[PDB]
Image 1 (cartoon, chains in turn yellow, blue):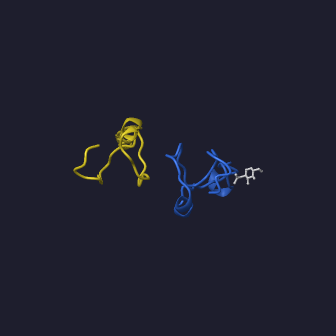
Image 2: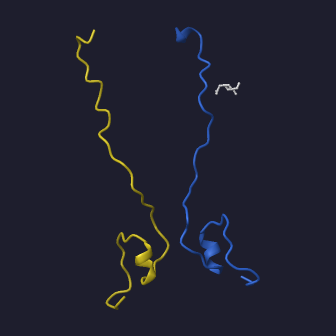
Image 3: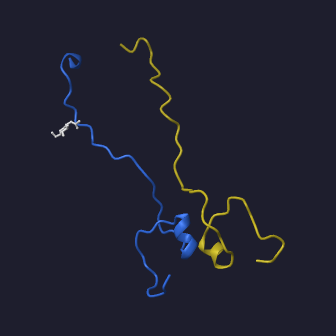
Length: 50
Length: 50
Ligand SMILES: *[C@@H]1O[C@H](CO)[C@@H](O)[C@H](O)[C@H]1NC(C)=O
């Protein structure tokens, strides 16, 4: 909003409050909230499972 | 570009060449190319099946 620089090449989410005053370019990447989970580790088999 | 119309909400890509002559907005959804294929059915074979 002041003037010490006119570029900021860093992940800076494009949002309404950040768009009211700042001016943004086209998005060069896409984001999104997604879950994370311990994958199925394995069968964990006991040979005496019979 | 003739100004005979105004805001035109419809499918319209944000490609480079189109942006050269007209202005755009921030996209209201994002999409790409994806594989379309038939659901598996399961008319399973002979010998192998048993
Ligand atoms: C399952 O049934 C449909 C309708 O007969 C058929 O088109 C398809 O080939 C069968 N199997 C597969 C590969 O989905």
